[PDB]
Length: 53
Length: 69
Image: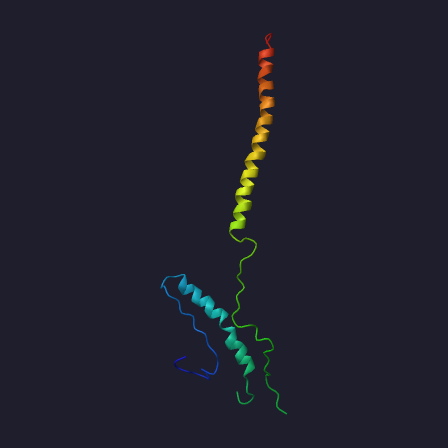
């Protein structure tokens, strides 16, 4: 969200942040990353301008 | 004509959907079947032990009846 690399902020991102610094909540956010990652891949399929490689 | 990779989304695969939900068991209803099986369990078992008593006294009666033994 802070530093764009190649066409960012235009794609909708969801970042999971917990509360406790234990191993379980540090695992839950990784699965929550995985469920909120297809949103980016679907938006990548939605926006594809044909041109140079 | 230029042919490149085409874009397709259609249904968008549904971005983050919950699949985990409460099924079968509710809470209080499981205790009615749980403790209910226990009360049915003892009542069925103890009636057989009363039927065992019919055999028990009759088994020991054979020893009393047999004196030539």
